[PDB]
Amino acid sequence: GEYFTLQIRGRERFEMFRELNEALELKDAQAG
Amino acid sequence: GEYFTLQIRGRERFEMFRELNEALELKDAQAG
Amino acid sequence: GEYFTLQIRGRERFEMFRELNEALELKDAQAG
Amino acid sequence: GEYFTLQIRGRERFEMFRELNEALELKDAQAG
């Protein structure tokens, strides 16, 4: 639904969360 | 180090990532 | 590559990690 | 409560999940 932003400290941590978020979005995309 | 922002879709997902991020920050805080 | 097991406490936390792991695996599956 | 195990593929992914799980457990430990 709505969008939220999360501030993250550190490039490695950011990359980790970005990867996780993209994977969840790819998974969601499979049903619509 | 530097801060990054990540846009997340959905309140439940946002809450999940927020929880994870806070936990990592609490863990980091234990050595400084 | 190799497989590792992680013991998790709590059904809700387990479900969260399972979801994340499945999403990453779905993402990986897209290139092979 | 109860414990569950999750099979994970890849050492780097395993380490990432282990880190996340330990952080959540550290966070929980702060209220009991």
Image (cartoon, coloured by chain):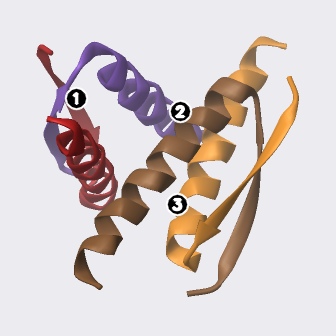
Chain colours: A brown, B orange, C red, D purple
Q: Is residue C7 above or below residue B6?
A: above
Q: Quadrant of the C terminus of chain B?
A: top right
Structural distance between the alpha carbons of marks 2 and 1:
14 Å
Instruction: Tell me the residue that label 3 is attached to.
Output: B16
Q: Secondary structure at mark 1?
A: strand
In the image, residue A23 lies at what x, y percent? 38, 52
Is residue C7 shown left or right of residue B8? left
In the image, residue B6 lies at what x, y percent? 70, 54
Q: Residues within 10 Å of mark 1 (few under 14, many from 20)?
A: some
Q: Which residue occupies 36% across, 17% down? A: D12
In the image, residue D11 lies at what x, y percent? 28, 14
Instruction: Tell me the residue that label 2 is attached to.
Output: D23
Q: Is residue D20 above or below residue A19?
A: above
Q: Which residue occupies 60% across, 34% down? A: A15
Amino acid bearing label 3: Met
Is residue B18 shown left or right of residue D21? right
Pointers 3 and 2 in contact (C-beta within 8 Å): no
Residue B4, visible in the rendered structure: yes
Is residue C3 shown left or right of residue B3? left
Amino acid bearing label 2: Ala
In the image, residue C13 lies at what x, y percent? 34, 53
